Amino acid sequence: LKSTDDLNKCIDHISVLIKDAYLLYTNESFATSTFISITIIEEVGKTHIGMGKDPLRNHKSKHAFGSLPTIKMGGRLNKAIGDEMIDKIVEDAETGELISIRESSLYADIIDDILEVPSEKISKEQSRALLLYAIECFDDSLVGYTHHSFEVSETTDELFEKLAN
Amino acid sequence: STDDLNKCIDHISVLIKDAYLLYTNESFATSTFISITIIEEVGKTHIGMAFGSLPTIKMGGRLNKAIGDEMIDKIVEDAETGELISIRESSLYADIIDDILEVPSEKISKEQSRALLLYAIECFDDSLVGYTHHSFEVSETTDELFEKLAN
Image (cartoon, each protein chain N blue to C red):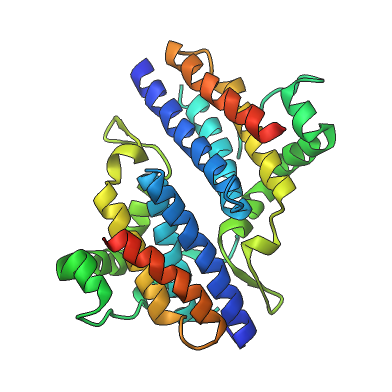
């Protein structure tokens, strides 16, 4: 992102994905919701590295999850899912277990030789946590630097409080 | 087992209800990502008994009437080219291409979103319906989605 025009385009894009994850989350597609939630976290992460057949596509994807800003204590996210959940999502982002979770949230697989289906590997509690983390690391990284960002964050904030309580 | 094939048909039913739910909330780009994903999963499931399925298209049948002959040739040509993989990428991920930032809402039209979902439901109906009794229940549901989305 090189201009305030590009920052506002990226904010609109991610605002669309948040509303899409929230829409699925309420219609009880926890699995699909979680797929979008982790995809939001990636995109936010990509802004921090600084740029579908790229030769380094999985190094950019790995680094995107590594360069997420630490969430400060005593914020709305620490009240909504608690400090141990946050550390489990962060450890999963720096390991790349988030990439596995994302894969298991959309594609059936045969693992051992049992068939495993997203519907049974992603729980409501993990769908809600990842969407709230997604909102909060978007609000921390991109919101506040433009006037546009405030109208977008007013709606993003309502989703956050609906979902947190 | 037919219990594992049923679990795969229930998964694909979920994705279709999600593409539909997103399409009717005007998230065309996200819908389209899910729609292309159903076509890959249908081709992967069927073989488990780049898109290996592709439904045989019957003239003046349901899909022909809903999206037209020309759009089916374009979707089939995009599926054999590997353009559909590219359209999937562009439908979820922002990209910088020749120094300008491109977002899914500028790459994916409502027309194309509708076509790909209708095509994805017909892929499902042509490949997996009728192997198991449960398949016919699920097909009944996807047949009302198809009619609500076609008109």
